[PDB]
Amino acid sequence: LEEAPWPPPEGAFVGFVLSRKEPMWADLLALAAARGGRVHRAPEPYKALRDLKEARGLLAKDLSVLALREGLGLPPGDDPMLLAYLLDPSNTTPEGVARRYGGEWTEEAGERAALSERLFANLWGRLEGEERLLWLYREVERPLSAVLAHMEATGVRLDVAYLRALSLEVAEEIARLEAEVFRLAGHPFNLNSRDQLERVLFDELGLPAIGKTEKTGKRSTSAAVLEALREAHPIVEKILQYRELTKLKSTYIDPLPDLIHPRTGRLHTRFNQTATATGRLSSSDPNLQNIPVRTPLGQRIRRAFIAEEGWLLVALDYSQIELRVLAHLSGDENLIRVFQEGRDIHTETAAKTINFGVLYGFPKVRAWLEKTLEEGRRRGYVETLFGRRRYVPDLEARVKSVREAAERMAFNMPVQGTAADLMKLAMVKLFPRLEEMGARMLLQVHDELVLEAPKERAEAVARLAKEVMEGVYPLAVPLEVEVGIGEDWLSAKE
DNA sequence: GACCACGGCGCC
DNA sequence: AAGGGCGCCGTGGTC
Ligand SMILES: [Mg+2]
Ligand SMILES: [Mn+2]
């Protein structure tokens, strides 16, 4: 490469080095661009950002997020991770991708920008002909990355003083349970230690081991095992409560307050777009897709996610997206009439534990299942309604437990992959319309979305987002969305 | 201090 | 609903 002066011309690939992975917390240590043969290294990274028109490169969405916290509208566009990930969703990291498609992922910004150019070449080449993957790329994954960049930049508001109060309460009850259990044991021990607990239950007290752990073969102390021993001994219910409280305190109540961003007053996740085997997003640092919901204490934690003052949260949930998608994929004239007729699938068919089990093993269903394994064995991958693929190679393993595990992965992906393609497309469609009404998209939770709207315009945003989500891509069966509205996530009623 | 494997468990 | 998909915690441990 011919090392050239900043700035680069239109359309260059960008490479950048961050002091850490979270773009909302990162310092920009270096910035470069590459096009043709030349590398352009920016003398001053942050000022240099202003001269870009869009982010084009490996991890584009991360640079667009950093740009966005700094006040600049720099959207991402082309990203070789996205194409690689469409080709094989086992392509999740730039290290892997680089090694696979012709480069080395290093820590130097110039070499990353170069790397980007050569990789996109090599990958856009592997997508000539793959016309459905090209479509998910142009119409879903590339535009979506702009939307997730803005969601990440915006963040969600948290009531800290509430969480600090919950924390003291919960520390008090933890103390009650732990004293309870130590006396029952006749001695004190580390209750967060599954090994010392295991000695207590099974060696010291007389209780029956029910399961062994996978990798090392210790007697399990999982919830399953403890539920099975609930009647056997009073120490057990206490341990179950202790686990519950300490899980929620260690994972949500204590750390989340400390992640509030000084400049925004909000919490900012990463929505990872190339992290999953099925085309779902993941969320990390912190994960906001696993905020508690089933227990009382869980629901009190969920009250802590709140709208800005004067706004409201708008929570929208697809009603059994996966069964409805199974109806469309399999074409079972019967299962479709069940949804088209507005009726509750769980009633017409105890039974919920067969509607949901048949995802993993009504005849067009079995037919669908069997055709899926066959095309999986033949081609080596299965696919979604939109043609997203997951390669499942052990479908022909000669060990039954591995083949059968593989079959379960193979069944699952077309339905999970499809529900995901749908939610992804629907975010892409919904985003620009929310902006037009000054509303925000805050979170995605697989088949749910959380938006924030000015109180005055909330019922109208909810009406609009519902129709957009319901009509995203009509299928033999209707997609149903439940909408809720409220001042906190629990009241909004997701 | 950073990283690790494991068991365990939060959500979809 | 979680025989599928995730990410995060503390422990016991290395380096
Ligand atoms: Mg829900
Ligand atoms: Mn599972």
Image (cartoon, coloured by chain):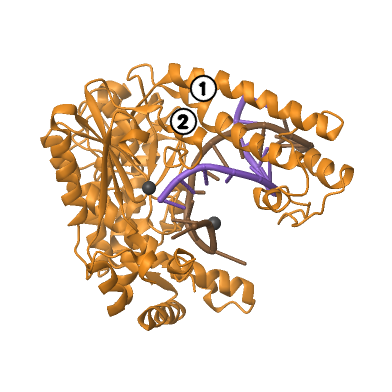
Chain colours: A orange, B purple, C brown
- Left or right: A79 as drawn, with respect to A393: left
The part of the image, by quadrant, that contains residue A486 is: top left
In this rendering, the answer to whether A159 lies above or below A409 is: above
Residue A6: assigned label: none
Q: Are marks 1 and 2 in contact (CB under 8 Å)?
A: yes
Residue at position x 51%, y 22% in the image: A166
- Residue A257 coordinates in the image, percent (x, y): 46, 22
Q: x, y (%) of residue A165?
A: 50, 17
A122 over A265 or under it: above or below: below
Q: Is residue A225 visible?
A: yes
Read off the residue under disc 1: A166
Where is mark 2, residue-wise? A301
Kind of residue indicated by mark 2: Ile
Residue at position x 28%, y 28% from top?
Answer: A67
Distance CA(mark 1)–CA(mark 2): 8 Å
Which element carries disc 2, helix, strand or loop? helix
Q: Nearer the viewer, residue A41 or A62?
A: A62
Residue A422 in percent (x, y) is at 27, 57
Query: Which residue type does callout 1 highlight?
Result: Leu
- The residue depicted at 12 percent of the width and 34 percent of the height is A437
User: In screen coordinates, is A375 left or right of A180?
Assistant: left
Q: Is residue A209 above or below residue A18?
A: below
